[PDB]
Image (cartoon, helix red, strand yellow):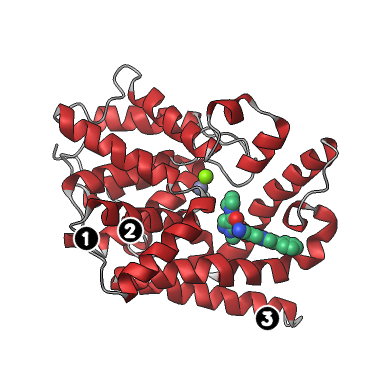
Amino acid sequence: GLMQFTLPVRLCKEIELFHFDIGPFENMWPGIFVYMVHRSCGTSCFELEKLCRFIMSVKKNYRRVPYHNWKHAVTVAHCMYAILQNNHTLFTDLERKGLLIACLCHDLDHRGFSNSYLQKFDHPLAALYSTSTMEQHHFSQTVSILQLEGHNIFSTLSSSEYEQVLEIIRKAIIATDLALYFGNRKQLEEMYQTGSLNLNNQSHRDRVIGLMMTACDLCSVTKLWPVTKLTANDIYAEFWAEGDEMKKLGIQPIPMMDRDKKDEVPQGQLGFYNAVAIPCYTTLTQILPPTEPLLKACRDNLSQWEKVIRGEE
Ligand SMILES: Cn1ncc(C(=O)N2CCC2)c1C(=O)Nc1cc2nc(-c3ccccc3)cn2cc1C#N
Ligand SMILES: [Mg+2]
Ligand SMILES: [Zn+2]
């Protein structure tokens, strides 16, 4: 109970900032997550023994893939930590509990392949889950781990609170299906601009949490340029492997996944910042003004990709 996690001075200070990188020391990531749960939620939110056992089982069920790995999970959780900490009063006790867990679990058992590839492969998961295939799997893996003996971190919650938090987690994980992001943001934009956005409306809260999940999931574009650039390498390492596997099925992959078209990556990133990232952080900043640093960092990285195209690097 009187056992706080404490980080070294540089991490203690920089972990509060949106652009924090969790670093290359894998063994410190569990402790970083617990630290964030303690400050974001409270030292009482979870039994430390159950939480630690949950974290280590989640880690074990992330795979050794270039991008959709345990580091991504903790990175996405930290961005949620920064949003929650800069929006103290806007979120319920159950939301703060569920959302850091949702982020840690949101890509559980990812193989480094898109929903499209599972469907074209005719993977069993595509028969079990026709839409948001991997995201329904991620939620299923989250429930599986929560039901392991000594892993039920929500055991103190009432039966109705337990159902509410698992519903927050399910919606939050489904929302990380980028196919659903476009429509979600359009609705939020209209609601904000016609002034009809109401944070007491549960359907509205659900939409806002969805956008937070997209924002956290894409947060590689909100880091300092060297982090953004080196993360982009891991992303394309997966995309190009999927492209190779598409070619093995006798299907020409989209250019994004074709390693023969490495040259077009800079222009591909511009499209991504303009069509997905900038719109995402703009709408998020309109709804949650203290998240503006994410939009500012995103714009800085768009400018860096423009410089790459002009051969200034
Ligand atoms: C940074 N970031 N973080 C997440 C994602 C992402 O999607 N994720 C995570 C799993 C799903 C990205 C990303 O980079 N996304 C895209 C890159 C891209 N390159 C080209 C491209 C076209 C032509 C030629 C070469 C590349 C097209 N593109 C479309 C994209 C989208 N959407
Ligand atoms: Mg995902
Ligand atoms: Zn993710």
Would you say 244 lies left or right of 293 here? right
Snapshot quadrant of residue 265: bottom right
Which residue is found at the position 75% from the left and 49% from the top?
A: 240
- Give the answer, above or below, for where 81 lies relative to 191: above
- Name which residue lies at 40% across and 31% down: 142
90, 42: nearer the viewer:
90
Q: CA distance from mark 1 to mark 3?
A: 40 Å
Can residue 74 be seen here? The reply is yes
> Tag 1: Cα neighbours inside 10 Å, few (<14), some, or many (≥20)?
some
Identify the secondary structure beneath mark 2. helix
Percent x, y for residue 164? 23, 37
Residue 126 drawn at (x, y percent): 60, 31
Residue occupied by mark 1: 199
**Relative side of 92 to 102, left or right:** left
Q: Dot 3: few (<14), some (14–19), or many (≥20) neighbours within 10 Å?
A: few
Q: Which mark is residue 208?
A: 2
In the displayed structure, 193 sits above or below 148; it is: below
* Image marks 1 and 3: residues in contact by CB distance under 8 Å: no
Amino acid type of the residue tagged 1 in the rendering:
Leu
Q: Check disc 3 and report the residue beneath it.
A: 307
Give the SS element for disc 3.
helix
At x 39%, y 40%, the residue is 30
The amino acid marked with disc number 2 is Val
Quarter in which the C terminus is drawn: bottom right
